[PDB]
Each structure stands twice: as structure tokens, then as C-alpha cells.
């Protein structure tokens, strides 16, 4: 009889179903139409609940939680533009694999397209970007509970990667005391309510078969390219490449320890590309390669075969090489395609890489962002993790620093948005409970400024470095036209971040030299709170330093 | 020959075409893939160029510009999540009619679904929310310029209302000197380049016919309901209703002068609803009605016919009455269906409305948000405009204040999002160049916090009042469950806004009484800058005051 009561019973099935698929974290934004979902969530002891007022930040908070935990994370939002704000995080998850389960409250069908407040067309509004889309019907006891749980179980069970849009219409009344409406309906599921498994278990695995001719191919002159992978996978790939005697080109996101560091510089040297021309096979593990020189070499190389191993689906080679696209867990794949010890075939490149790093070290002293990137390994928190932002910082660290093998690195490098980096970092921290270093640019920090609210709650110290070069200086690295560059590309905002930190009662430092930076870090790691460290640098020094180093190494 | 040059020639045709359809403002966010569009725009002297770093805010800036100017406004963003961030403003425009032209740069077809950085599936990504969607092909001289301009002319010419998504793929290279590549291709348009008209003129008008039985219905017992309309339309509707002798229920968005004010209160009285049962016809002009009591009365009433007149398309009656949905400019419609002088038929409601206002007046003294809303008419800038935020503020002004006829009011009440109110207010100000009073809540201000960057550039004084009641106190008005209310609904953030103002070098006041508030107002109207006035109030006083006044008036 009670619509409000049945709404909550319907919602309770949805939420309990998710607990059977490893959902522990749920991120909730405020609203009224979402009440049945939010109250079901609040009442369910399985969840860790996170809240935020900006649904775009909420989506990215969820992204960060999923990124680190490798488990599906749920999101609840009310109807309207609240739903639209989830798009950026959903798109990124589609590219890098995070399992985001978006529970989006909706008006019932009778209030769509009739000028009702906060009512929009929500089914399909994320187009092809969710992996799965469920448009739930108007709640009714005439649809059995077993149908509802089965539909959720199909979506979660068959989810290899990416987001799920579950649209959830509810009619008013939304409020009122619970009565027994829908209880017998729920009880048709019997002791499933006390179970720890799905109602319907549907969990096919997607995996490429082992390559039977690997033992032939591993005897050839190969190159290993390591992109984004897990910290442990990076260590395994490093050992595997060494054993093969193949050069390892390691991305900043790879955690391989980058045995041939500064590839963005030495790949610019003709002696290196000449040697790499001898490669008959390239085996790339992971994807979303960072550096321009690596992307250019990848595009130009012409091995007999190009393989990409990764656990995400679809084509991952933007140069469309003849070869293989192998879907697998990287660690598992390495066990199936083991290395046998063989004499290394590269002679010139190890020397060039050493020389390249020496050239960077020679310029370590200036208090600039290139130097900060080069030295960043000196500031990584012990037993911690690094979250690297987009634009120049990820490129500078990739080109100029040698990050330790197995030290966890996280990022948003699918679509490389600058719109959710602070909120993502917050989720990254909360998921693992580890001390966290996050580094972002000034426009990036402004973009997600209100996520400083989230950083008021971290479980271990988090240092947020904001590199302030007054605008998007990546457009001083790119050959943008000088006449239009400041107004239409760089867009300097001429701000500092001391007042932003103060607004959210976060500790703040603006160090003016290396000694003050070291003192700031020493202060920051002492407590389970977020410290903002603003590094103010001259606009174009970072870009010019990279360019000068590129040129120097190309002449070695 | 030159891809970079032809990209810019292709883009120049797109941008020049827009100028023939009244596009003067263009809002641009930074990026590289957007270069052909952005350089074409920068070079075109027809445009007023606005920039911002947050694409969600950029969209709302454009929304505000369009809202006031009543012309199409263009937006340029780069590929990736930048495009997704335009969704909230596009959705709101779909509902309230703003013509937003979204030029979204894209990767070319050969770089989609292959793991390329910042490349996503963009065609159709806004689903059914744009009025028109154009997915442009990969640029080539083998497609003639006359096709490109004709497609743009079709989209703009036939655009009654709402957004247009124009997806614009460009292949690299994007940079390089202009040469003559594509010049002869452009010149196929001949002296269209020196013309002031579209290439293809396609502009059918959509309008309902004269109602031939209006002379019959205008003699009946009617009620006029006035929703959102232009300031001039509000004055016309007031005079028209007055002439007919029909009671006018005027929304805060109507600018009718609200001759029967506090309708949200007196509609709660059974005597008013009893009198309204006599209405044989209801003529509603405008839509998006604000108040709960009005929405409830509208839903319950049973006149022989219910008419809704508005220049927006589609059903606008969420109660689905028997009647008519008439598409027209409201001022035009009134001229086509003029009033006849007739004796007013309502007797009780004028009594109740006066009594309701006296009840509110009796409680005007406390320094609270209800009192601020009641008194806001006393503080409107001369020759200015009011921008009213969402949640409690719009409801309190609607329920408790009597706004002057023809005094411009602007709002985002289609989807009623709290995600873009500051950036929308900026656009509203820039469009008219008028002194602006903007009022929003604390979560709303946090949501669009970085839009304070935009408010650093206003052409006349803008007073931004932030009502800080520590959370979304609309959920103290709604019957939300007390146990979950704070954590999962109200979400207090426990901040103030002095540091936010300081960050963007905006003047700031936190007045503690009316004298200090009036002093702040006086100072603020003196210069063409934004002043932030933070009104800190006890969390639940506003909601409770509204609840008490409702009860008091219901018992009259
Ligand atoms: C949501 C979004 N909008 C636009 C872009 C394009 N973009 C890439 S880098 C960049 C500049 C970032 O500026 P900042 O954070 O100051 O970093 P810097 O370039 O100075 O290193 C922009 C606007 C993007 N990647 N994501
Ligand atoms: C983008 C978006 N997310 C969520 C909502 C639901 N909602 C309506 S009002 C409101 C609270 C706004 O809080 P505040 O700005 O402090 O205003 P107050 O309720 O205190 O008047 C919320 C979350 C919305 N309208 N838009
Ligand atoms: Mn910067
Ligand atoms: Mn509030």
C-alpha cells in the first residue's frame, strides 16, 4: 500500500545485491529523489560511506577509490544535472577500467517531458560510455524481486572493466514511516538475504590464449615497453626484460624502476633509434604511454610484430601495427610466457641513457619545476604512493626522474582530464590508507578547487604540491602561436593558494628554496592530514629546460 | 597541401557561418585539439571572446550570456572530458530554451578506440539533449564549403530553442604557418564572405494559431498563473489579468508585480482552494512554477480547460490536464487574445493574500534568511537585475516577498541544478551590463567556487550574497528522517567565505545586523566590481519560519 515503503524495499534489494559483488565503498551526494537509495545505503552495514556536494568531484572520488582498491565502487546521486556531472569520471573509467556503479535516481515515467522540476531524460544519457546500462522500470510488486536482483547480478557479474549506469526511477511519496509493504515481496528471495553470494552467478572470464610460438619469438631481438600496470607487475616486468636481454623502455606509470631512464631524452638521439631499428618484435605491457619521444618512436617503429598485453579490452596501438592484442592480467601473462636467460643485444642505448641522466643531474640545482620533477624520488613518502597530475608534471617526471621499482604510482591518464585530480587523489588516499604525495598544476588545482573539502579527511598524511607557473604552461612547450598564446592557451589566473588552504583549515607552505621545501615535507608527514605546498616558479622555465635537455641529449 | 592550414580554413567557415545567425559571444576553454576553432574564433572580429579554465563553468557562463541576450552563444572546448563537462549547461538549455552552440574539438576517426590519449567517442555523447546534433566529417577539400556552411545554416536557422552539438574532428598537424591551402576552396563561396546573411536561409516559424473561441472563454471564471517570462511580458500579463478580473497567481520568476503575494502561504488555506474550485478555465503563461502550494494546487485543480502559453515546446503541465498547449511568444499571444474589461469574480482570495503578507511582515525583524528573502525588494539595485539561486532562496523569495513588476529576474530553474550558479550569474551580468544582485546558498557557492575567478571581471557592480546556514537546509524543510539528516542530506561543510573572496581579490563583508548589511550594499554599488556578502544564519531558522507562516496562514 505504501509507495514510500515499497520504494525503500526495492532500493534495499539493489544495494544488498551490490554487496555480493565486492562493493564496499559507496559515494553519496545529497538529494531528495535519491532518498530510497541513500536510506538503503545508510542502513546497510556492509558499506563505507563517503559524501561530497559536487557530483563531478564525487564521481572522481569514486574513481580514485576504485583505482586503488580494484573493486567496484558505487555512487548515488539525485535526478537532474547531478547525474550529468558524473560523466567525466565515467568516461575515464571506460578508458582505464575502474568499476564505477552509478545509481542515478530518476523521476518516474509519468513526470518526464512534461515540464516537471528537475526531471530530464536519463536512460542512455551516457551513450556508449558505460560498459553496461540498466534502465530500471517504475517500481512495482508485480515485478518479482528475483528479476531485480538477477538484472543487477548480470551487470556486475559480467563486468570486465568500466562503468555501469543503473537508472533508478522512484515515484513520490518518498518519505514516511516504514510499514510492511513489500516485505513478503522481499521474502520471496528466501535465505538469499543471509547469503554471501549473488542470486545469479554469471561470471565468465575474458582472456587471450597463451601464444604457442612465444618460445620462437623470445629468441629474436625484442624490445619491452612498459606502460601503466600495478606496482608488483612493474617489478616482474623489469626482471623479465632483464632475463630476456631486451631493452626495457619504462613509463613513469610502470613502476619498473626505469633501468634505461630519461627515455624521452635519449629516444631523441639517432644512435638510439638506429639501434632500435634492429628490433624484430616489440612486446608492450600496459598502455597510455606518456612521453612524446616514446609515442613518436612507437608510431615509427616497424618490427615484424607488435604485441600489446593489458587487461583492458580493445585496440591499444594508435599506430595500428601488424601484430597482436592480448587481453590478460600482466603478471599471469608473464608466467605463461616466461623469459629464458639470453645475452643482451643492445650496446649503445645503455650508455646513452646513463649520459642522458647525467645531463639532467648537471642541472638539478635551479629551484624550478623541471628540477622538482627530477628530484621527486627524494620526496616520496616511505611505504607511500604517488598520484601524478596531468599536463607538464607527468611529462617532466617521466623525462627527468627515475622512479623506484615497485613504488606505487596512480594517475588519470585515460582521457588525461585536468578536471578531477584533487578529488581523485582523495579517493586514492582513502582506498589504501597510505601516506600520499599528489602533484598537480595551478589550473588543475583551480579546476577541482572545492575538492580541498574532501582533503580535510585523509587517513594518513597527504602532501598536495601545487606547481604554480601561472597558466597552462604545457602550451609554452607546444608550438602554439605567440600572438594568441597568453589569452587563448595559457590563461594565467594570477592567484595563489594560501587562502584556499586557509578556507579549508589545511596546513600550507610556500617554500622559496630546497631547504624550505625539505622542511615543509618534514613538517607535513607528521600527522594524518593534508598539507598544501605551493611551489611558485617562473612561467616557462620548466618547458624551456625540457627543450634544452632534449636538444643536448640528441647531440650526444 | 598543409593539413594545419586547411584545418583552420575549415574552422573559419564554421565560425563565420555562426556570425550570420546572431552569434556575438563565444566562450573558449584552453586546449590543443581545439586550435583550429580557437584560432579561427580569435581572428574573427565579429566576436566578443570570453575564457575560463573550468569547462562546466564555461558552459554556464555561456548559458547566462544566452539567457539575458536571447541570442545564440558559441562555446569552444578541446576533446575528452572537457566536452563532457558541458553537459549540465546543455541540459538546462534544453529545458529553458537558451541557444548554446557547442563546438567540440575531436580526434580524427583514425585515433578513436585505439588507446590514444584524450580520445573518446564524442558523436552522440549528449544523447537526446541537444536540439540538433552535427557530427562533422574528417576535414577534406573533397567536401565543398557550400556543404559545410549549409549544414550549419540548417542547424541554426531551424533552431527554435536549446543547444546544438557540433562535433569537430581535426587531424594533426595543428600548428604551422598559414599558406594558401584551402583558399580556393573557401573562395567557392564567392561574395558570401562579404555578406551579412546565411548561405542557406531556412527559418520556418513555429507558432500556435489564434484560438477562435477565446471570446467565449474570456467571459468565464478564469485564473491566470504566471511562470517564468520576460520582464516586459510580466507587466503585460499583470495588466491583462487585471482587465479580465481574473486572479493572478504570480511566480517569483514572473515579474508581474505579484498582486496576490505570498501565494505559497494563502494557497494553503482551504477557503482559497474552495474559491478556486469555481474556476472554469486556467490560463498559465510561462512555466517552471516555483512554490510547493502552487504546484499542489495546480495538480489538484479541475477546470474545464487548462491552457499553457509559452515559447518553449512540448508538454509543460505535470498534472496532464485536459486543455491546450499553445506555443507562442507571450507578448504576441496576449495581443492575439486580448482581454475584455470584466468584473473581478474572486472575493476571498484578495482578503487572504493581504492577511498572509501582514503575517510575514510581522516577522520581518529577525536577522535571518527568511527575513532577507521577504525584504529583498527593498534592496534591489536601481536599473538592475536579480539572479536567484536554487534551493531555499528562490522558495523563500517566492513565498515571502513581493517583487516589483517588470524588474528583471533570472534563474536556472529548468533542472534547478546547484552546480553552475556563480558562472551563470557572471554571464547574466556581462550580457546586460547591469548592476546585479545574486543570491545563493553555501553549498551552491562551494559547488561553483572557482567561478569567483570569472566574477573578477564584471562591467557593473555585482553583489553576491552567500546565505550560509551550514548545509543544504532545504532538507530541513523536507520531511527527511532525522537520524540520517545531517550526514546524508544536509552535509554541513563548516566553512566561511572570507578566504575565497580574498583569493580572488574580491571585497568581502560578513554583516551582523541590518545596519551593517545596508552599509555593505551602499559601498558595493559604488564600483564596477563583485562584492561578496556572507550572511551567516542559524541553520534551521529559515525552514522553520516558512513552516510556521504556512501553518499560521492556513488557519486564517
Ligand atoms: C577537463 C580538461 N580540459 C582541458 C584540458 C586540456 N589541457 C591539458 S593540459 C592543460 C593545462 C593544465 O594547466 P596546469 O594545471 O596549470 O598545468 P601546466 O600545463 O602548467 O603544467 C589543459 C587546459 C584537459 N586535459 N582536461
Ligand atoms: C547539481 C545538483 N546536485 C544536487 C541537487 C539537489 N539539491 C537541491 S537543493 C540542494 C541543497 C543546496 O544547498 P545550499 O546551496 O546550501 O542551499 P539551501 O538548501 O541551504 O537553501 C541540493 C543538494 C541539485 N539541485 N543540483
Ligand atoms: Mn600551470
Ligand atoms: Mn545552505
Image (cartoon, coloured by chain):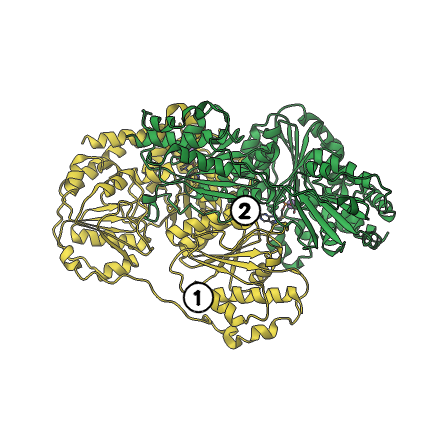
Chain colours: A yellow, B green
Mark 1 sits near ligand 2, with its Cβ under 8 Å away: no
- Residue B334 lies in what quarter of the image? top right
Nearer to us of marks 1 and 2 is: 1
Question: Which tag, 1 or 2, sits closer to the chain's start?
Answer: 2
Label 2, residues with CA under 10 Å away: few <14, some 14-19, many ≥20? many
Neighbours of disc 1 within 10 Å: few (<14), some (14-19), many (20+): some
Mark number displayed over residue A54: 2
- Closer-to-camera residue (B43/B77): B43
Chain of the residue under the numbered disc 2 shown in the image: A
Element under label 2?
loop
Cβ of disc 2 within 8 Å of ligand 2? no
Q: Quadrant of the N terminus of chain B?
A: top left
Q: Which image quadrant for residue A463? A: top left
Q: How far from the left and from the top, in percent, is residue A69?
A: 41, 57
Q: Is residue A438 shown left or right of residue B351?
A: left
Given residues A182 and A451, the one toward you in this image is A182
Going 47% across and 69% down the picture, which residue do you hit? Answer: A150
- Left or right: B546 in relation to A427: right
Per the rendering, the mark at residue A332 is none
Q: Which mark is residue A154?
A: 1
- Whether callout 1 and callout 2 share a subunit is answered yes
Residue B520 x/y as whole percent:
69, 29
Could you tell me which residue is drawn at 16 percent across and 60 percent down?
A213
Q: Nearer the viewer, residue A158 or A117?
A: A117
Q: Position of residue B311 (x, y in %)?
A: 64, 41
Q: How many marks?
A: 2
Amino acid at each position: 500500500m505504501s509507495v514510500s515503503a515499497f520504494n525503500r524495499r526495492w532500493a534495499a534489494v539493489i544495494l544488498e545485491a551490490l554487496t555480493r559483488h565486492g562493493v564496499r565503498h559507496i559515494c553519496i551526494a545529497p538529494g531528495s529523489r535519491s532518498t530510497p537509495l541513500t536510506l538503503a545505503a545508510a542502513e546497510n552495514s556492509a558499506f563505507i560511506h563517503h559524501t561530497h556536494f559536487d557530483e563531478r568531484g564525487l564521481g572522481h572520488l569514486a574513481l580514485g577509490l576504485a583505482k586503488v582498491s580494484k573493486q567496484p565502487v558505487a555512487v548515488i546521486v539525485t535526478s537532474g544535472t547531478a547525474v550529468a556531472n558524473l560523466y567525466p569520471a565515467l568516461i575515464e573509467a571506460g578508458l582505464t577500467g575502474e568499476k564505477l556503479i552509478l545509481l542515478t535516481a530518476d523521476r518516474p515515467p509519468e513526470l518526464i517531458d512534461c515540464g516537471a522540476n528537475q526531471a530530464i531524460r536519463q536512460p542512455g544519457m551516457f551513450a556508449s560510455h558505460p560498459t553496461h546500462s540498466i534502465s530500471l522500470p517504475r517500481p512495482t510488486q508485480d515485478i518479482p524481486a528475483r528479476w531485480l536482483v538477477s538484472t543487477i547480478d548480470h551487470a556486475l557479474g559480467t563486468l570486465h572493466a568500466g562503468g555501469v549506469h543503473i537508472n533508478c526511477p522512484f515515484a513520490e511519496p518518498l518519505y514516511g514511516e516504514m510499514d510492511d509493504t513489500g516485505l513478503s515481496w522481499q521474502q520471496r528471495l528466501g535465505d538469499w538475504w543471509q547469503d554471501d553470494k549473488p542470486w545469479l552467478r554469471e561470471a565468465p572470464r575474458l582472456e587471450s590464449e597463451k601464444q604457442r610460438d612465444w618460445f620462437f619469438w623470445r629468441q629474436k631481438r625484442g624490445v619491452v615497453v612498459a606502460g601503466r600496470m600495478s606496482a608488483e607487475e612493474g617489478k616482474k616486468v623489469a626482471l623479465w626484460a632483464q632475463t630476456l636481454g631486451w631493452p626495457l623502455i619504462g613509463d613513469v606509470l610502470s613502476q619498473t624502476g626505469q633501468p634505461l631512464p630519461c627515455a624521452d631524452l635519449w629516444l631523441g638521439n639517432a644512435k638510439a633509434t638506429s639501434e632500435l631499428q634492429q628490433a624484430q618484435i616489440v612486446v608492450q605491457l600496459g598502455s597510455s604511454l606518456t612521453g612524446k619521444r616514446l609515442l613518436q618512436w612507437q608510431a615509427s617503429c616497424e618490427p615484424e610484430e607488435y604485441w600489446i598485453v593489458d587487461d583492458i579490452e580493445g585496440r591499444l596501438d594508435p599506430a595500428h601495427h601488424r601484430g597482436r592484442r592480448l587481453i590478460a592480467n600482466i603478471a599471469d601473462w608473464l608466467e605463461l610466457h616466461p623469459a629464458e636467460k639470453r645475452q643482451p643485444w643492445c650496446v649503445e642505448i645503455p650508455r646513452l641513457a646513463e649520459q642522458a641522466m647525467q645531463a639532467v643531474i648537471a642541472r638539478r640545482d635551479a629551484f624550478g619545476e623541471a628540477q622538482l620533477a627530477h628530484r621527486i624520488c627524494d620526496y616520496l613518502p616511505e611505504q607511500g604512493q604517488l598520484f601524478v597530475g596531468n599536463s607538464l608534471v607527468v611529462r617532466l617526471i617521466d623525462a627527468l626522474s627515475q622512479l623506484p621499482a615497485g613504488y606505487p604510482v596512480y594517475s588519470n591518464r585515460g582521457a588525461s582530464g585536468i578536471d578531477g585530480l584533487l578529488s581523485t587523489a582523495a579517493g586514492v588516499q582513502r582506498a589504501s590508507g597510505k601516506p600520499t604525495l599528489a602533484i598537480v598544476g595551478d589550473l588543475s588545482a583551480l579546476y577541482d578547487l572545492n575538492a580541498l573539502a574532501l582533503l580535510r579527511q585523509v587517513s594518513a598524511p597527504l602532501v598536495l604540491i601545487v606547481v604554480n607557473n601561472n597558466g597552462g604552461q604545457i602550451f609554452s612547450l607546444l608550438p602554439t602561436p605567440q600572438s594568441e598564446r597568453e589569452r587563448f592557451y595559457l590563461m594565467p589566473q594570477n592567484v595563489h593558494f594560501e587562502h584556499a588552504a586557509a578556507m579549508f583549515e589545511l596546513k600550507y607552505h610556500r617554500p622559496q628554496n630546497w631547504q624550505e621545501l625539505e622542511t615543509a615535507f618534514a613538517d607535513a608527514w607528521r600527522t594524518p592530514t593534508t598539507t598544501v605546498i605551493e611551489m611558485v616558479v617562473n612561467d616557462t622555465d620548466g618547458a624551456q629546460t625540457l627543450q634544452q635537455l632534449l636538444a643536448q641529449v640528441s647531440h650526444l
